[PDB]
Image 1: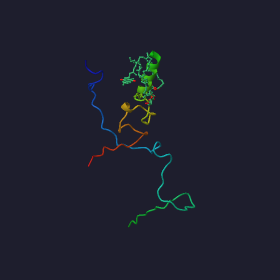
Image 2: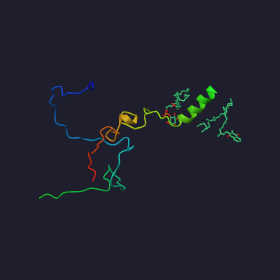
Image 3: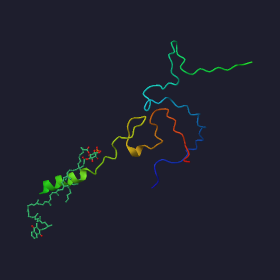
Amino acid sequence: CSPPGETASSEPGTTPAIWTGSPSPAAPSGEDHGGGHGAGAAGAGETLTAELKT
Amino acid sequence: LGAFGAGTLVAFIGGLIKNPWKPVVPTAEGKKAVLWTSGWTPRFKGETIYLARAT
Ligand SMILES: CC(C)=CCC/C(C)=C\CC/C(C)=C/CC/C(C)=C/CC/C(C)=C/CC/C(C)=C/CC/C(C)=C/CC/C(C)=C/CC/C(C)=C\CC1=C(C)C(=O)c2ccccc2C1=O
Ligand SMILES: CCCCCCCCCCCCCCCC(=O)O[C@H](COC(=O)CCCCCCC[C@@H](C)CCCCCCCCC)COP(=O)(O)O[C@H]1[C@H](O)[C@H](O)[C@H](O)[C@@H](O)[C@@H]1O
């Protein structure tokens, strides 16, 4: 006997889309954070960069 | 004798017997039995399982 499911079905297929993972509910109960500070405002954390352009 | 033998053999063996289809492996679709899963089963939705090489 042959297994029930095989063969292409003459269907070409499509290139897999770039993977975009989601946050981890099972492992992380909440959303992890980076830098910490007092941040008495809307929220900036302990990490804020800048780029100087000409 | 028959009842005692049945009970004693059940007592011996029941230690060994393990339900292979007890849902033990956590999965994005609820706990599942081991044979239905592997390291590639997404433990949570959208989980990124990298094809990591074994150096
Ligand atoms: C949760 C869990 C695993 C629980 C289980 C517990 C566990 C791990 C183990 C124990 C479980 C079990 C299997 C318990 C029962 C053990 C067992 C086979 C009991 C049988 C006893 C019984 C039910 C008797 C029913 C009444 C009846 C009709 C008795 C007459 C017929 C029988 C059974 C005769 C047996 C005769 C007998 C004990 C022979 C033993 C053979 C041996 C090693 C030696 C014989 C022997 C003897 C006995 C001498 O006294 C002696 C004295 C001086 C010189 C020489 C000898 C000699 O050669
Ligand atoms: C004549 C005997 C009449 C009784 C028939 C025996 C079979 C009936 C089973 C009914 C119980 C099912 C519901 C409740 C129970 C349930 O759900 O358990 C199941 C497993 O059934 C058990 O309980 C242990 C089974 C008992 C051993 C039976 C051995 C077969 C018999 C037929 C052979 C000896 C009898 C004499 C005949 C031969 C005569 C010789 C001349 C699944 O395991 P699991 O959910 O993982 O839990 C695990 C725990 O069991 C486990 O002890 C523990 O070790 C952990 O593994 C745990 O993971």
